């Protein structure tokens, strides 16, 4: 199979390290497509806006349809996510993974370049929809590819280090937003590492599991000897692409074969969609809990962006031995019991508000780090379609429902949204962390996992 030859080969070799840096340079490009609107949505105030830079609000005249503008903008981005979920979930299974990712990166690069010189607001909306759709496809495909590519005992290292790469992408976005004469300079500076990825994407291999599922043993042997020659060692071909006698046709029934696995997979994928929805809603509620500003213009966003590194390092230290479901329970209970304190009286002589908000964030970031890792480890039949469906098709619902509901609630009553978010999160997502599946150090992706699971 793949795990035995991966253990017999260098799982963390130097070629693996340069491929890791290349897909990390992919990972830092996912910051502004999801969170960079805060650096593009400055609203300082015949309408005159006093700011040395500019924004979309300064560019247009958003004084009577300002609420109709940005809400529809982010709703169209999340609709682009909604199309892109099913789109890449079937397209990666159809035309493979690596060529899909390369073409999708090229489309992202040309779409960002054309976004930098957007003529009209209709072009703005269309390009934002296409950008969101493509960028979500790129990031999820890259994360799945490198989760599969690394060996058995080093999945978490890769996953947590790429969440760290996303964090340093937000940090570099905050550092870049200091030099903001127009949004165009920011977008043009962001779009250049995508071309760097395209330039240095000629020396990256495919996914051995998906390639082996195509019964192409020759190119599997080719990529194994390429990996061995890159590390400069003779490969101990114990299996020699044995393929475990796999002959099942790829994409036989994506999400249609779950009827035979109803008592064993339906409840698991349901609780996974529940946990994704809870993470998205709680995350957005904690961002809007101050409305992305608290006495500052950039320091609040840095506090909401540099908080991920302590959570990531805590996860990397913690989840090696205790498992991957107890971290879910600890993170969920900590987030709930941290956000529940804001109902109490504000700190008269201390900083309890920022303390509970930062520890709640830490809990939510530990939860989001894991949700992706356990999703990649699970859905053993085909990790692409089902994994994207649980990842993105129940996060776009959070993106379309969560800001409108909490905005209207904070317009009418502060107490209801925080209480409902805390109750739903704490109770339901702590019940959700009650072993959806048995955890194993190995990472196979065959249907034998679905029918056995140890
Ligand atoms: C990257 N995007 C869109 C997030 N909202 N991240 C998140 N922690 N839910």
Image (cartoon, grey):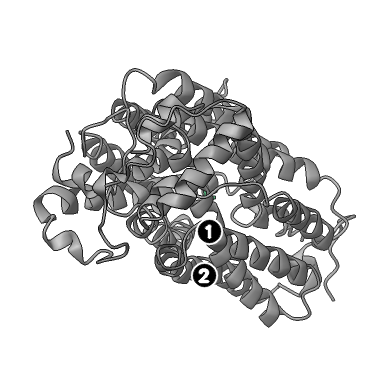
Q: Residue at x 49, y 30 (%)?
A: 362
Residue in the picture at 54% in, 66% down: 133
Picture coordinates of residue 449, whole percent (x, y): 21, 42
Q: Is residue 137 left or right of residue 193?
A: left
Q: Which quadrant holds the N terminus?
A: top left
Q: Residues within 10 Å of mark 1 (few under 14, many from 20)?
A: many
Asked which secondary structure carries label 2, the reply is: helix
State whether label 1 is within 8 Å of ligand 1.
no
Q: Which residue in the protein does label 2 denote?
A: 80
Residue designated by label 1? 136
Q: Position of residue 108 (x, y in %)?
A: 65, 64
Residue 301, given in percent of the width and then of the height, sits at: 66, 41
The quadrant the C terminus occupies is top left
Q: Which mark is residue 186?
A: none
Label 2 with label 1: CB-CB less than 8 Å: yes
**In which quarter of the view is residue 71 placed?**
bottom right
Residue 144 visible to an observer of this rendering: no
Q: Nearer the viewer, residue 329 or 322?
A: 322
Q: Residue at x 36, y 53 (%)?
A: 387
């Amino acid at each position: 199979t793949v795990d035995d030859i991966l253990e017999q080969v260098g799982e963390s070799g130097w070629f693996q390290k340069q491929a890791f840096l290349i897909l990390c340079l992919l990972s830092a490009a996912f910051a502004p497509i999801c969170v960079g609107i805060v650096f593009l949505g400055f609203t300082p105030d015949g309408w005159v806006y006093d700011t040395p830079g500019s924004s979309i609000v300064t560019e247009f005249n958003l004084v009577c349809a300002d609420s109709w503008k940005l809400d529809l903008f982010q709703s169209c981005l999340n609709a682009g996510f909604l199309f892109g979920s099913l789109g890449v979930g079937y397209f990666a299974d159809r035309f493979g993974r690596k060529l899909c990712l390369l073409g999708t990166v090229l489309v992202n690069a040309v779409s960002g370049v054309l976004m930098a010189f957007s003529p009209n607001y209709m072009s703005m909306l269309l390009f934002r929809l296409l950008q969101g759709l493509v960028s979500k496809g790129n990031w999820m495909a890259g994360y799945t590819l490198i989760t599969e590519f690394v060996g058995s005992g080093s999945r978490r290292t890769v996953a947590i280090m790429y969440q760290m790469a996303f964090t340093v992408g937000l940090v570099a976005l905050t550092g870049l937003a200091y030099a903001l004469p127009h949004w165009r300079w920011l977008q043009l500076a962001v779009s250049l590492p995508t071309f760097l990825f395209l330039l240095y994407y000629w020396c990256v291999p495919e996914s051995p599991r998906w390639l082996l599922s195509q019964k192409r043993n020759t190119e599997a042997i080719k990529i194994m000897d390429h990996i061995a020659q890159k590390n400069g060692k003779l490969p101990p071909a114990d299996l020699k692409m044995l393929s475990l006698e796999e002959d099942v046709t790829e994409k036989l029934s994506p999400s249609f074969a779950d009827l035979f696995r109803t008592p064993r997979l339906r409840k698991r994928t349901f609780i996974l969609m529940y946990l994704w929805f809870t993470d998205s809603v709680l995350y957005q509620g904690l961002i809007l809990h101050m409305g992305a500003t608290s006495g500052n213009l950039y320091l609040d966003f840095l506090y909401s962006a540099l908080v991920e590194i302590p959570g990531a390092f805590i996860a990397l230290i913690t989840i090696d031995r205790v498992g991957r479901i107890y971290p879910m329970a600890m993170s969920n209970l900590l987030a709930g019991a941290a956000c529940l304190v804001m109902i109490f009286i504000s700190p008269d002589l201390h900083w309890l508000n920022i303390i509970i908000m930062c520890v709640g964030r830490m809990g939510i970031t530990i939860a989001i780090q894991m949700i992706c890792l356990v999703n990649a480890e699970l859905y053993p039949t085909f990790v692409r379609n089902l994994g994207v469906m649980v990842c993105s098709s129940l996060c776009d619902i959070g993106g379309i429902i969560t800001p409108f509901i909490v905005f209207r609630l904070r317009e009418v009553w502060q107490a209801l949204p925080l209480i409902l978010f805390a109750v739903l999160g704490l109770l339901a997502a702590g019940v959700t962390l009650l072993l959806p599946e048995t955890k194993g150090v190995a990472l196979p992706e065959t249907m034998k996992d679905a029918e056995n699971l140890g």
